[PDB]
Length: 223
Ligand SMILES: [Ca+2]
View: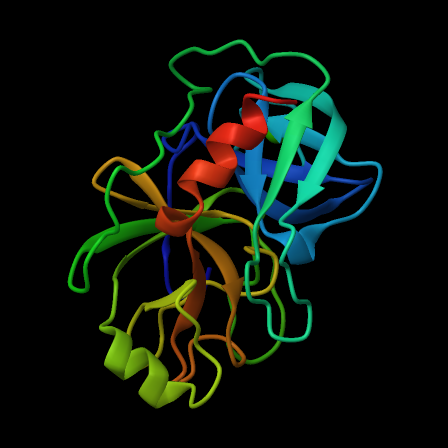
């Protein structure tokens, strides 16, 4: 997260870290046994880390659970990142509390102008690299579809939306991928891609979770 603020330990209880020896992506706990992330985050040997603030320090509220199954969306295209969404089942159900909580899926697609919260452990710089240990948070509006397609000619699909600021300075970034975009208490997006980070006229592009609710629900019900 570039240009954000420190969230506070466990203030974002649905945020998760995907770990394969090291943090490489974020995710969202949507029930006690399932996590949503970005398909381009796929790899084998994932351990899901719930309850994290400093991902380099055991602080007391962590739950470390291995994945038993990863399900990339059937129509994921790694060239275009269309349908950048993946489901992860935990080997064991998490223990849900104040600090480890699921986030609800949407009944409705959120509209442009809605303010949302983005979070993750990604790069905090637009030029160069400095990765934080504690969770970073960004409030940002969904941008209209027209602005989004204007900034990214020929690249936005019905399954993506832009959020952020055309002026630059505030954005998600590398290492935030897979993480949550929450609007009015609902998971509306997944950190997916962008042209650099926090550049002007290059806002962040997010998977549009409101299109995948039925796939998520019938996938969870059969696995
Ligand atoms: Ca920790």
